[PDB]
Length: 314
Image 1 (cartoon, rainbow, N blue to C red):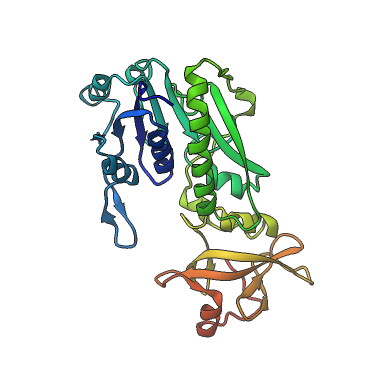
Image 2: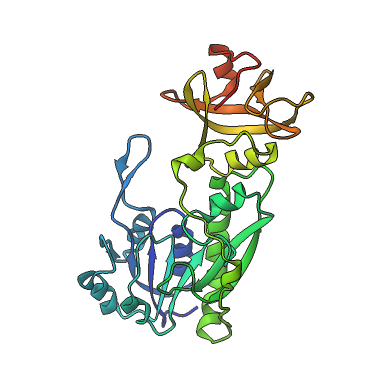
């Protein structure tokens, strides 16, 4: 909108990059960027400038990377910049009341769920895994309590049949940067009406513990399918075969003709073996990663293991 608007952006991963980029391309005066310290990435676990740090330094925007922004010395740096608006996206630090109460047009967050649903760290994983009809982006005010601030704007994004969590990440990120661009002028011009969240309707998308990665074969084949794709490609669901913990990357929903006990390998095909579930919908594992081995298609796995029918997983 205007170069008259000083903006500070706070974000770390790739999710936040389109948000920051769109802010810049919009013409806003981005005076500073706050990102997390650089953390190891990849198979090799290499230390790497955060995706936001990289994008920011392409423009020559100063990057603050405090261990904890909630500390005086660190947040005073931010207070010094005197931003008129603070935007955050996927910023995993506690923003102090001092910073919150500071800017003229408030501190706004771009959140990857339709609040008050799926507050917290893993709303994208949760939406898919819960077999959500549609998810979206919420842009709301930042307060003390996590994701509990008044809602400014929202947008809906459909979850397609073959969506992975990683693919919805890009979709929600792209839709977030857009909604923000459409939001900021409306916000500043007072055309926006903050909607207090209904605490009755609040659900928390808590961070995925390893015990939640474990495939529950007892559930419907429809649920196991959304469980597998909802954890793809981070942090990936797992099960057990021949004693090995096997990361299950992908599975297809296929009919099982004779209803058997869940977890049982009922059918063997060319591209994978079929496993029984809690209902009429079976799950054919086509892509998997046994412990200590690289990710592979079940086609290659089958050639080397051949788990015979009747064997149970888990």
